[PDB]
Each structure stands twice: as structure tokens, then as C-alpha cells.
Length: 398
Image 1 (cartoon, rainbow, N blue to C red):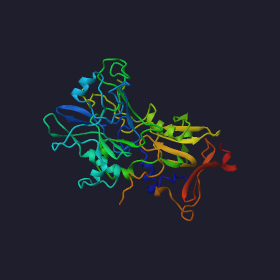
Image 2 (tube, rainbow, N blue to C red):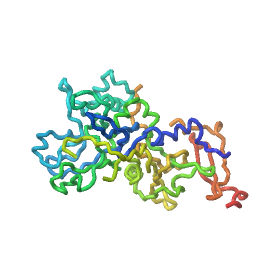
Image 3 (cartoon, rainbow, N blue to C red):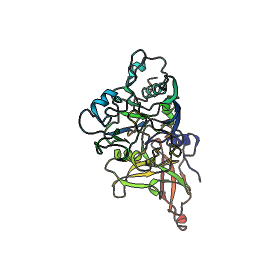
Image 4 (tube, rainbow, N blue to C red):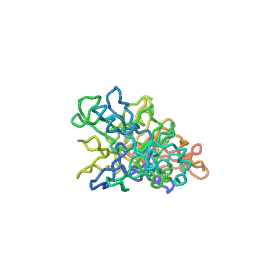
């Protein structure tokens, strides 16, 4: 056989869902992939279709009252900012209230579970849906087409709608970090994922809630236990450790590799390398970057020849897999969890499965440049895709 066993229709859809370019279609680190007009001015907008697991915005407020360094805090009141001085106290969370004097964010899941205008079949999805219904009001109090990002906190079952859509601020000329410099309006912040903290948080653009059931099958929300991502060249599946432009960095735990997919310089991002107190959204500029999901988004935990924990990070959306029991594959979008987390299980994958009787063993031609060949088979109910030795005959072209 000459052909990618993963190029099957069922398998291609499977692999395709790892492709940030293909469904997400916006930055992951910073997501500002759309622009909407509000009150004459044009503003950047989180646009991405996939929820990102474990992402939060880290704050660099000064370590003293009234500062909390927690972006889930209400944005500051004029008075609260008067009483505090610079910089802004509070967080990114929308503190606006209903005409009926009810309060929009956070919002208890139980209420959403018992609202009939919310159709989404999932817990996470319901909250995404809630974000999508939440359009900005203009400066003559009308509905616009601008929508806020959302963070569902699963541990507390609260759905946060974020008034601030800014995801990154850098530079002493622009913001203070720990009140250095001193009289600056804005503290600094950045998107972050941790090996240990905030796995109960899920950052998404409201547009994740457009068709709030889609991301269940189109987004790479879990991690792949037992495979390395890889690309198909020369009739066999090269994992990332064989691709020249990949990054090989030592980690102590898989958790740390998972963070790196999100954290490396080159992860898909919409933030350019260079603000009033009241200004919650980024402005449009003529040349601002839209990654459109392009970037070093992909990697896997694995062990060296010498059993050194290492992490392979790549630009290349995987179009095949190398089976490896102790490896796990991560995207900049997905969680650390290898199993479907039960907040995206409706109360109301299969692609990787096989039987030997149906799926014969197969051998490709020698990839002479590496003197290995592809070997596909069915081992213990699941596709095995490895590289193995070429035959003696074949070896005489290496």
C-alpha cells in the first residue's frame, strides 16, 4: 500500500478536528479575529469557534488592597477607581445590570438549566449560548453586533461574561506591572495556562455559542492518550520529532507540555508587538494581525531514547498518528484531560477503533531517507500506526 491509513473519510474528519485553522479560525492565545462597529468606532472582537480549556488572563496589579489579581472581578466603578487611585482595581467581569435590576455576570448554571430559551445540550455549551445572546449596548442604548468573551468556571458552575475583551497588555510605556511604573492607568496582563491552576476555567469567544452543540464534535477538547500527532510524507507517518521545524523541549510532566502548546512564542495569536480607564475593548488598526488560527499550536508529551520527558511542538496540523502508549497529544485549544469531561457530556473517539478481522495489517514502501517503513494494524481494538525496519532487499536503497 502507498496510502495514509488516516486519509479515510471517518479518520480525516477525526484528524481535521485538531486543525485550528479549520474550525476555530481565530487566535487561541489572544483571540481578536473579528471587528464590529459600535457607536461609529470599529472594535476588535473575539471570534473563535472553539472553547479553550484552561486559559485565563493573568493580572499584574500591585500586591496590596484593594487589588485582587483576579480577572473574574467586576470592572471598577468610577468611585471605586477614585478611592483606589492608579491603577484600575477590579477585573474584566461585566458588572452591568438588567432593566429588571438583575445582574448579568456571573450567572448560575442552575438558572440556565431552567431557562427554556437556552437550548444547548451541554453544561459548557449552555454558558456559551448565554454569551452569544449577550450583545453590547451602544451609547444610545441599542443592540449592536459586538459580543463579549465568556469564561465558564466549572468548579463553581458560574458563567462569566467579560466586559473587557483585551487579552494582552505589555510594555512600561503602556501598563504597570506591580505598580512599576507608578501612576499608570492600566496594570499589565496576559493569557495563560497553568500545569496546576484554573483547569476549572474555559475561555471562549461568544461565537463558540452560535451553534452551541457544534464544538462537541468539531473542537479538540480532550487530549489524545497513546498517540503522537504527525504528518504524512514519503509513504509513512512522521511524528513531530522527525520534522525539522519542530521544537523539542524538556518537560518534567505532560502537564508542562500541554501548557507549552499554549505558551510558546509562536502559538496562533492576534496580538501586535506594540488607553483610557473606561476603554474595555481593543480598537481596530490598519495592519493588525489575524492569525486565523495559524501557529505553533500542536505538540505531544513523550519519552526520549533515554526516557527523558520531552515535548514536541509544531506548526503542522496533524494528518496522521504514530501510536505510542506513553505519549499524549495536546493542542493550544484543548484541556489536559484525556477523557471526556462530564461538563460536555449531554445528560440526553469511535474513529480510532478497529477489529483485526476487518482491518488487515499493512506495510508501505521503504522511506529511503529514513530507512523505515509505515506499519498499520489493529492492536487491542485500536489502530496501530508505527515505523519499523525495512526488509534486507529494501535496505539497499538507503
